[PDB]
Image (cartoon, coloured by chain):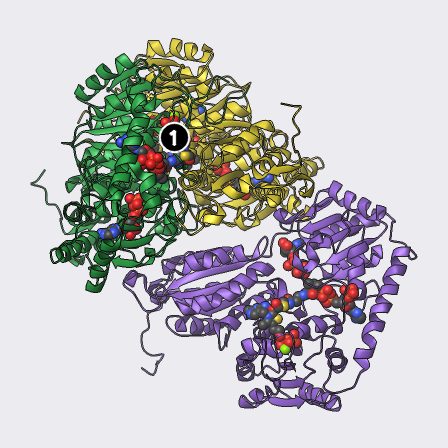
Chain colours: A purple, B yellow, C green
Amino acid sequence: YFQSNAMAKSEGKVNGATLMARALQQQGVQYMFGIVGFPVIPIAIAAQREGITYIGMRNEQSASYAAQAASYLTGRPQACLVVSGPGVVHALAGLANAQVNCWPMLLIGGASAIEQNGMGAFQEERQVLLASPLCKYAHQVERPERIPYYVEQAVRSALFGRPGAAYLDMPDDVILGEVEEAAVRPAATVGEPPRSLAPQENIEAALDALQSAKRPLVIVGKGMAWSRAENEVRQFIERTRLPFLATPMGKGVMPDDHPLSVGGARSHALQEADLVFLLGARFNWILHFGLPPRYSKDVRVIQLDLSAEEIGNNRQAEVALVGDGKAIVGQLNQALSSRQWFYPAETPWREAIAAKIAGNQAAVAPMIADNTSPMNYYRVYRDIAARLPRNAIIVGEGANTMDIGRTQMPNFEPRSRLDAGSYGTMGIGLGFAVAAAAVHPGRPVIAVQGDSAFGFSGMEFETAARYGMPIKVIILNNGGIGMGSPAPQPGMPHALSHDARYERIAEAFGGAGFYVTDSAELGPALDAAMAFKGPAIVNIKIAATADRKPQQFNWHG
Amino acid sequence: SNAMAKSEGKVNGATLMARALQQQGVQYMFGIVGFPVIPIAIAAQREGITYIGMRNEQSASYAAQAASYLTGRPQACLVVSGPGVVHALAGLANAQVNCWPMLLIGGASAIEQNGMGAFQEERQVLLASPLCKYAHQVERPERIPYYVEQAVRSALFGRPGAAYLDMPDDVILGEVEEAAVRPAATVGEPPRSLAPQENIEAALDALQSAKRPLVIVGKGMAWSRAENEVRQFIERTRLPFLATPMGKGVMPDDHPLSVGGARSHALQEADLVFLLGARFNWILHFGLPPRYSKDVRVIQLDLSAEEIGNNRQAEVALVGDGKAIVGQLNQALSSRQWFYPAETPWREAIAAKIAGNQAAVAPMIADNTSPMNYYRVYRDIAARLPRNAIIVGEGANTMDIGRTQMPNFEPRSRLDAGSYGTMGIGLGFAVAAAAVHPGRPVIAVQGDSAFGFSGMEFETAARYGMPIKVIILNNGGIGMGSPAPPGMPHALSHDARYERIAEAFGGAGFYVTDSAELGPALDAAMAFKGPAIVNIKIAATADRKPQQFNWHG
Amino acid sequence: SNAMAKSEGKVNGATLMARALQQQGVQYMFGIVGFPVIPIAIAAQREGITYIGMRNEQSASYAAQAASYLTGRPQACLVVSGPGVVHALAGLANAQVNCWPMLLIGGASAIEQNGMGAFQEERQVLLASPLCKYAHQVERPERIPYYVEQAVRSALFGRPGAAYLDMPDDVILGEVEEAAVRPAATVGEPPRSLAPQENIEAALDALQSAKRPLVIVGKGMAWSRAENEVRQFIERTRLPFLATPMGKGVMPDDHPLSVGGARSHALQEADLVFLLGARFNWILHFGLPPRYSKDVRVIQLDLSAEEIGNNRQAEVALVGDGKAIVGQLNQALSSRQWFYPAETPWREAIAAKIAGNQAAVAPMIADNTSPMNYYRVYRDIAARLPRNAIIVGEGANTMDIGRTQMPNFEPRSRLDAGSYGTMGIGLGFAVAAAAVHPGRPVIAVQGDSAFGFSGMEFETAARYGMPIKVIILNNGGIGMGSPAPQPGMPHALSHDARYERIAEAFGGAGFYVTDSAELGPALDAAMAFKGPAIVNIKIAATADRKPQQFNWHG
Ligand SMILES: CC1=C(CCOP(=O)(O)OP(=O)(O)O)SC(O)N1Cc1cnc(C)nc1N
Ligand SMILES: CC1=C(CCOP(=O)(O)OP(=O)(O)O)SC(O)N1Cc1cnc(C)nc1N
Ligand SMILES: CC1=C(CCOP(=O)(O)OP(=O)(O)O)SC(O)N1Cc1cnc(C)nc1N
Ligand SMILES: Nc1ncnc2c1ncn2[C@@H]1O[C@H](COP(=O)(O)OP(=O)(O)O)[C@@H](O)[C@H]1O
Ligand SMILES: Nc1ncnc2c1ncn2[C@@H]1O[C@H](COP(=O)(O)OP(=O)(O)O)[C@@H](O)[C@H]1O
Ligand SMILES: Nc1ncnc2c1ncn2[C@@H]1O[C@H](COP(=O)(O)OP(=O)(O)O)[C@@H](O)[C@H]1O
Ligand SMILES: [Mg+2]
Ligand SMILES: [Mg+2]
Ligand SMILES: [Mg+2]
């Protein structure tokens, strides 16, 4: 028909796709990243009918990574939408990554029709089984009338407690099945994650422990960024005058330019601290397990975590603070108003930290200042860091490209750096940047990737161009994974294409491409890329043997 | 000979495991020995751990979680490779559903033989993982202190659950240098957390506003060891309360504020419910019609934030430890005058429904005619229940009627089929209670079908001098009897002489068919210094009192 | 009243399930009823299926796979949701390891309550899947014929194994129109495959060239119903053979060509081994040193291609059905004159070691001391075992010594702990053998520990009038007795236990034996008693098996 409003239309019935779209919108899902196909086309269409922003990606890998980044950036679970069978299996990448990083996510996976189960149906798969080991919550929606219930429970399970991934299986007959409107049971709106507080004796014992320590170190993790505790943490550091270290994605909770940051003397600080205060940060590989040879064997630990089971992993916790980061630091701030202790302005600990920071700055100064071409990493970031706005979102991915950018690119706002994370994952790059451009379109999004990392997700540049996302992709091409290689005899397994013109990919989709080989070219290329009104790629050819500055300890062992 | 030089520099995995378990507070180990866990049980006893050898790993895995509940620390179930671990999956699943801690130590075939078809080779970690909070294989003996500490912590901290350690034969017998073994920290008490002060005040204001309030006291408060705080809270507020099946005893059952005798009316008519460590699962009928008002307001105290607002939204969420939060509530109550008034229409309706149900079952309690009904039988059982006894209840009618006729006056003093509705926990639970609290009498009241699942464990009780008192209510079938016959699927043996099983292992056996025999038989069984079975032949068609709603649907 | 108008156009899930099960040849259902499977058991009886109500789901699941092995068709285990299913995982795992078919039907909570914390809500398909060849939830009652057909076929065809059907409560009670239900085909006999002719001929070439050949008869041949072909093959080739524990009976244990009494020498010295439906797992010592020559040539017949060449490479592979391939071997041998010669140095060495092992246990067999040793006990047992009896053996010393002292003359007549070394199969296996073959005697010989795992199923045998004869060898411990305790030893049990009184609790006959003079009259009264019976024998605490060069495990 031409949908003449004069025709009688029954409004009693509603299908599972529409019920799913309404339940999602009610639960605060604003962004849905995916790829359509059988049987989830009606879901994405109904989502747009309710005002949800649908972002069609180029691979389910990037879609599942984008949804957890968007969840991290908004504070509520956002959705990944994938087709049955291989759609879900490609999306297991996001679930595993979200599980390891304690980020929420909602994977909506279509399934083949229930009535054809056992028959070898198109894309028939045991989807709940496969997803369950990676999920905090996984279930199949068996009938469309239960959809509000299942969406409510899946969002609550992903968001409350230690966050994780939720998976909802949607069979075809459920997506298309219809039920009476009045017969659909309502579901309550999931609110904010419940915050819990620590007992008072633990709050006072924490402050008691801090006073006794000669060389105390506060470690700020991305659990404080997730808890939205930046104000409380900045008040605590300002009030106590304690030295602090930020984790990779903990950067920005405290501003990177804060004078109390031991960032430039990280190895010395971990080695010589007699007491560590863990704020939303695990003693996993990223903090070298809290054990020798990176820490003192007798290091005392105050540990603030939402997960009671994490307390005392690897290295025992003297003072355990189990609860919400924002709430517990608020408790600490209120107890410090009854006390008057602060960490003194002049101690040997402060002197050793300042001297080591200056030594590390003096060690990288010649590399930052060296204008020879092909350029090293520190020289390239000199021009990048000079042009990064104070409110930018930075996505970093690679090995040397990522690790050197971690120290050369400051963050001043929390939740403004997205990188390989606790799983050390390549492939999150353009997925994370697309999520950052959809969640905060008023802020510049700059992705700085190595040449290898770009190849995992570089095709999502089309997605950015398709939705008018002015994402700035900067590629540091040394021609290999972690390091370049000469022309050979077969090629090295770590070898790629040092002469690749990755910037031409931008021209395929209507973006701007720039190619940098000499130091004099870098400045004008970056300025034009930031000023170009759309997505851009800047492909920088760096020295094949460029490396990070030498450290006493390898980052891994 | 002590004059012979003997190298003391090395220690094997079985000894490291026993030392690590003793350090983390494991005092009881239930299992069945065999390849390759024999040295583990031997090493455990040398460290002072009490080892109890059962007759089936099913009962062993149930005993381990029962003792964990009673002691407040994870206790051990030790089983052999292959079918040992698969037999023990029953207990892991039950522990997961009840949120009880548990440490299963499972032997495994030697790692050097993986893929060859070794004796009892199995993917044991993979099988157990979906039923556990924690599951891992110990790959090298030097890691044992680390893994024992992490498993005990994972099972005990937060929402408790099952932890599993896979112990290959080469790790059990593998030796390492004693000085090279890295020590682990001792897992302390479970961390407690509190609610925000705003939430404490919102909870108290909501209690003041309600016209028909009801406190529901769950076994989570028994696990939290929060009985003192709960009794102060109920005594301070004068609020009516309902105890869940194993929440019984947190408040004494004879307390004047209990709505136990008017449970259906209390849930149906309340306008506000205060859930204390209780879930809106099937046991509480999901907090939804037809058993509740569609507009019921909910204050929900739970340690798990993901459980908040399941099935029925919570108006006030109190996320944290039960004892700590009720402690906060008691403190905030010390600055208010409010208490629930002594005279309200809500109290009078509760009292009239209690008196109604009492008159309904009074003729069955007093009826001395034989074959007896359930209420007449429990009239003599209840009269001889010591107040410090640990009561194990198991069956359908036998358990459900025992739940109302057998009061508890202390917490953690009733063990029953639980949140999983499990038959087969009876003697395993009773064995665990007798090992943990040998100074307390242990009475298991089972139906005749329930006794069939684990009845062989009576030999375990006798072998260890555990004076467990097993009382069997024998109607001749599952849930109900049946006339003489193919036989009905639910039918069993109405004439079975189960008490003769006691006489097979030195216990005392008593057979009762008449009401005049019940009193003297219970007294002779209670007095006997050893285990005892009282087999009672009840009426085939005896049943529970009529109700408006079926317990399930 | 039949005069009342009754609508007969609808049928529910439990009835569809019963008709589907009976259509697919399910004759026996072992379970324990309760929510939500009560209608399924009642419906099964209406279609003539024999329902046996057990006392624990553990035994129920072991019973179902034993009946599948004896009947050649998957039989049912029926369990309630939640812990019923979790208790039955033991049988699935044991059926998987032994390659025996089995159909587990598990009730489930109603689908419409999923996620709510319903009574006995559980991820039952997820838990059972690693142990099953086939595991699915029946989502709608109209699908029941389809799923039953697919599950029985998946459990029975190819390498057999367990199948699991999850039956939610709203599917059990749900109704469908009679004429709307889609029919399902009847699963027939398992497909048999043959070997290429060049493999048949090369296998025969290998046999001729061997100086010390050995044929190993495994329970794969028993499951394939290949006893006729195997007997014709050993009789035609005159080859020495060794039967596995449950391969016993495929060839009569009294055949002159059995090397059973010289087992270690036959494996150690054979230059060529012909595996007939037997794996080189722990039971055959992996086919490797120190139990075999390092250069041992292997011919391997197995239905599973992936099994071929495990641990020890096979010189000739025969992938197919046991009955079918041995038929090819017998056919090809009719165009050959070769047979293994009547007199060989290999034959004399086998004879000598048998004679030496016979003389090694002969004094223990004849020793009339009380407390008795194991061999003395079995002298009276074996002298009273009917030739058509079904033997169930379970324990450590009790089972291993019963293996050599109780011959089997027919196949599929011995049921024991199997490839998984499982305790707890005893009375479930005996109940299944009594239900399936009620005209045949069923004798279960268990140790004291093993009887404690399933002893309560004696009430099941008494309730269904199954004349199972339970002989318990009580040494007062697990594998060995123990002196009185000071904490009791972990392996210790009750040497003075009167296990036979359990029989008197359920109407059976109980007998107690301590002296050797009492053993004879007690066994004769137990066999003559018209019903189940327990013979409790207090054996010596330190009695052990014949000394061997190698330990059974390592
Ligand atoms: C390839 C790879 C990297 C690229 C370094 O090369 P790239 O050009 O991106 O940066 P460079 O160091 O400046 O050369 S890192 C890394 O861990 N990894 C292994 C790796 C591969 N795949 C996935 C999913 N996660 C990974 N973690
Ligand atoms: C058999 C069985 C019961 C016995 C009632 O019969 P019993 O004689 O013990 O008590 P009665 O009511 O006085 O006659 S209850 C029940 O749920 N059930 C099913 C059931 C079976 N197996 C497992 C593991 N869990 C279960 N839950
Ligand atoms: C207890 C036990 C056995 C009894 C030997 O003692 P029993 O009195 O039955 O026989 P005895 O040797 O004549 O004294 S064997 C064994 O492997 N095992 C460990 C064992 C335990 N649990 C399971 C499920 N499977 C097992 N396999
Ligand atoms: N609201 C919250 N309050 C406190 N801690 C939290 C909260 N949410 C998550 N966490 C914890 O923060 C920790 C983050 O650790 P990790 O991912 O290792 O951070 P990083 O990698 O920055 O060190 C997790 O262990 C998680 O349990
Ligand atoms: N220390 C604690 N404080 C408060 N609640 C707890 C604690 N430990 C466990 N819980 C919670 O108590 C609840 C027990 O509820 P449930 O087992 O349903 O009780 P019942 O069976 O008596 O209704 C679980 O949801 C669990 O998360
Ligand atoms: N019809 C059949 N024909 C041939 N082999 C079969 C058949 N069915 C099963 N099998 C095989 O028989 C083998 C049984 O070996 P196993 O259980 O090790 O027996 P045993 O313990 O007697 O050695 C399995 O590998 C299985 O694949
Ligand atoms: Mg590179
Ligand atoms: Mg009964
Ligand atoms: Mg024994």
Q: Quadrant of residue C328?
A: bottom left
Front-most of residues B536 and C72: C72
Q: Position of residue B344 (x, y in %)?
A: 54, 32
Residue B544, position in %: x, y?
34, 27
Q: Residues within 10 Å of mark 1 (few under 14, many from 20)?
A: few
Left or right: where C418 falls relative to A417: left
Residue B548 at x, y percent in the picture: 35, 35
The residue depicted at 26 percent of the width and 41 percent of the height is: C243
Residue A363, x across and y down, in percent: 83, 72
Relative to B543, residue C247 above or below? below
Q: Would residue A326 be seen by someone viewing this image from the given angle?
A: yes
Quarter of the figure that contains the C terminus of chain C: top left
Q: Nearer the viewer, residue C220 or B63?
A: C220
Furthest-left residue in this view: C3
Q: Label 1 marks which chain's residue?
A: C
At x 58%, y 63%, the residue is A76
Apparent side of residue A195 relative to residue B270 in the rendered image (left or right): right
Q: In which quadrant of the rendered view does residue C318 lie?
A: bottom left
Which quadrant: the N terminus of chain C?
top left
Question: Compared to B124, does C541 lie above or below?
Answer: above
Q: Amino acid at mark 1?
A: Pro
Front one among B536 and B202:
B536
Numbered disc 1: secondary structure: loop
**Image point (28%, 26%), residue name:** C458
**What residue would you read off at disc 1?**
C547
Q: Is residue C190 visible?
A: no
Say above or below: A27 vs C37: below
